[PDB]
Amino acid sequence: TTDPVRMYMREMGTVELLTREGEIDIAKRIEDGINQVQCSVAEYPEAIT
Amino acid sequence: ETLRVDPTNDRLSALVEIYRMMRPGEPPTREAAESLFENLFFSEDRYDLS
């Protein structure tokens, strides 16, 4: 098939929908890592100042 | 001799292969293959109504 629409829809067709806590879990892992980079800010050299 | 070369003798394979000719590379789903097969050229929608 030459079409990128078949290719793309078959490729998005690979991964499924993860719902109702994996969304909030993505959000929680995201915010956790974020919180830890601002920890890394909290333990600063001149870089932050 | 055809059966000795090829063993498919079922309708649902007929319908999946219907899908597959109609929607090649696309995943056959049964109401899709069947609604395809039917609604295309026996629904009132298509035969516009003229």
Image: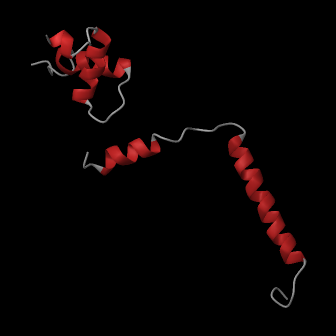
In the image, residue B11 above or below residue A11 = above
- For the image, the number of numbered tags is 0
Rendered location of residue B7, percent (x, y): 26, 12
In the image, residue A40 above or below residue A29 = below
Q: Nearer the viewer, residue A4 or B39?
A: A4
**Image quadrant assignment for residue A41:** bottom right
Q: Residue at x 33, y 43 (%)?
A: A6
**Image quadrant assignment for residue B4:** top left
Q: Residue at x 43, y 45 (%)?
A: A11
Would you say B35 lies left or right of A31 here? left
- Residue that sits furthest to the bottom in the current view: A46
Rendered location of residue B24, percent (x, y): 26, 33
In the image, residue B30 above or below residue A26 = above
* Quadrant location of the C terminus of chain B in the rendered image: top left
In the image, residue A24 above or below residue B42 = below
- Residue that sits furthest to the left in the current view: B50
Q: Residue at x 21, y 20 (%)?
A: B45
Q: Residue at x 24, y 15 (%)?
A: B38
